[PDB]
Amino acid sequence: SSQIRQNYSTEVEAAVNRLVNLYLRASYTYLSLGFYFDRDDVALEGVCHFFRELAEEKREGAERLLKMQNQRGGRALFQDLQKPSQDEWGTTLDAMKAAIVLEKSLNQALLDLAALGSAQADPHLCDFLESHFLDEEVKLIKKMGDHLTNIQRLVGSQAGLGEYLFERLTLKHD
Amino acid sequence: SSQIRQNYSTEVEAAVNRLVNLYLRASYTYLSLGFYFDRDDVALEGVCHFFRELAEEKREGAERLLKMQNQRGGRALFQDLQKPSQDEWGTTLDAMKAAIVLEKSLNQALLDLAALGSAQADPHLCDFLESHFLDEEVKLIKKMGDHLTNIQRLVGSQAGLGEYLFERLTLKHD
Amino acid sequence: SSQIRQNYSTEVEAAVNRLVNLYLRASYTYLSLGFYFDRDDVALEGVCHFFRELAEEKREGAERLLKMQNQRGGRALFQDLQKPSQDEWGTTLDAMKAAIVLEKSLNQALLDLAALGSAQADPHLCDFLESHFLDEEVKLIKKMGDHLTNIQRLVGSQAGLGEYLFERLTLKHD
Amino acid sequence: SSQIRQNYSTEVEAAVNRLVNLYLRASYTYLSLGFYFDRDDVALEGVCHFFRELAEEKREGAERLLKMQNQRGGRALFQDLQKPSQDEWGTTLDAMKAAIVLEKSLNQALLDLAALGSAQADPHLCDFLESHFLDEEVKLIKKMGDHLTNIQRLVGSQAGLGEYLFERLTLKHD
Ligand SMILES: [Cl-]
Ligand SMILES: [Cl-]
Ligand SMILES: [Cl-]
Ligand SMILES: [Cl-]
């Protein structure tokens, strides 16, 4: 069973398993975004790379939560993973707007879990989120917000031109 | 406007702007202390260097707060910067006593902001202060306290001798 | 008191202290400009970097004046530092126009002090300004003028596009 | 005769020859100071080294003036060199006080020559002094003033102790 568990509430254990599901769902959403931008009829390499990187980051976040669950003596429980909300993701702008929505939802889940940890007097959990998740999320949301502003200023009356230039001159590509 | 702000209270935003002012004021105080000890009629190089270093440290603390303000989606607001409390700073002892007073005031402002963060359930802010400010301040206050004790033991009946020896043998100089 | 002062007028001493205030004010203005361009709703990294660099340059100019004040046996006297003239700085164009205004004001103050030095038969002061300030200021004003022309030619009927392209292709960024 | 002389007044030529004499006299004074501090009954190595270095510096200043005299097409004219004002130089304090007097006299001679150059519309001469002499002299006087303050604070009621400590802990020695 366990022999190590100490100060680790059933409420936190369940919430961690839920958060793993949310991160894996987010990873799957980013996988879909990445491959949409690799379509020959979309063909925005830097946009593809941006979202493929996020798919890996979210998977790694789920793995870190699972490692922690076992370190505390809780039990990983996996649930079905829903498919992403869209099959096609529109423009770079549409995609970046969907990404910031998704990140705000993950951030709120992190904050909710931090608040649960405080309520449960679980300082290890609170430390864990502060150390590996909260600032990573703030940094990423700031980056997306920066990108949104630049994408928006490039729409002008020549959306295609602006979308190409943003991909070429802001996003990382070969 | 903002598109990134989340869980970032107006109260914290304002308090961060106030703390920026306090750090910039402290930086200005240390600039004045540094140049006083470079006067030809004062001429204590190690004391000059000690306070010039602190002027840079406090400026960098203000810059880190400003970076964080933008990362969270708050808005930097700058106010007039008051001049330092003195134009001449007395002996090394007088200066180190003024410095520890100043640092206690910064430390209390940090603690007040940490308490506001806890009240507002803002774990990112609390993490931020713990990571970059609270221990730096404890370390610095301990160092100043150590220096005060050594300065005090050197006063004896030969203050000039003790002030020279402390500058030469404790403080870093060329 | 002093034992080193020679050929260093009270008029120059006071004017140097005033010029220190002007440089520190300019540094503060550039700090504000830099952080405005780091806002997520502005997000022009190269513009941010340009003005953050100038904030450091102006601080260093103030420090060089203070060092010189002590080398000549004058006494640094610090005054309150007024906040910058604006809290928000508009477009890159608006900001660069404000910067060239500011630099012209610093340049005129330098020239006024050079003329005072000549009047007071203070060749060390005149040398000092020529060596460390006058050409640095001419170079910087020429650079800003160059930038203004390029910004202006990019406005066209697509201001957002031009502002992005200038930041990407002229200014230094990561 | 000359074939190169241009814009080089007889007044400046004579004043340069006088200044050469003043620098060589100063060099001789420092030679005497250096060897006094090497006496077995004085024995302050760092003080000896300080003044021996200045003897070389003043000789080199005289050589630079002579080189310039020939570059401009003037004619070096050498006069008798008076012996130093003292045969024995007292304490480190007495010596440093005599040195700052001497340096103030050289500085005034430099300033007088700079003013003569301006009067004669001789910008090469004015540049020459600014480039190689005026700031070197300000720097040296500031250093001596710094030393005087430290020597004075060490007198206390134990002059011998203070004189030893200054030599050991401020001045450069083997
Ligand atoms: Cl579904
Ligand atoms: Cl005040
Ligand atoms: Cl104001
Ligand atoms: Cl004689």
Image (tube, coloured by chain):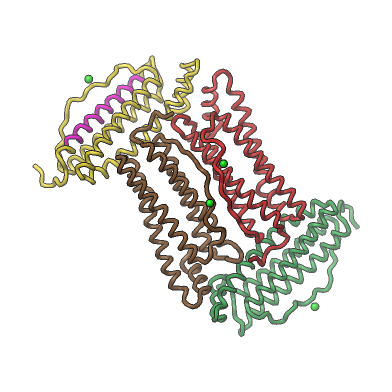
Chain colours: A green, B red, C brown, D yellow
Principal secondary structure, stretch drawn in magenta: helix
Q: In x, y percent, where is residue D63?
A: 24, 36
**Magenta stretch: residue D28 in it?**
yes
Residue at the (87%, 53%) spot, across then down: A5
> Can residue D20 be spotted in the picture?
yes
The residue most toward the left is D1
Residue B148 vertical placement versus C148 (above, below): above
Relative side of B159 to A124, left or right: left
Camera-side residue of C59 and A79:
C59
Magenta stretch: residue C133 in it? no
**In this orientation, which residue lies closer to the viewer: B71 or A4?**
B71
Bounds of the magenta segment: D13-37
The residue drawn where x is 49% and y is 60% is C50
- In the figure, is residue C100 to the left or right of B46? left
Q: In this view, does B74 lie above or below B140?
A: below
Residue at the extreme right = A1
Q: In this view, does C100 lie above or below D115?
A: below
Decide which of A123, B94 is in the foreground and name it.
Answer: B94
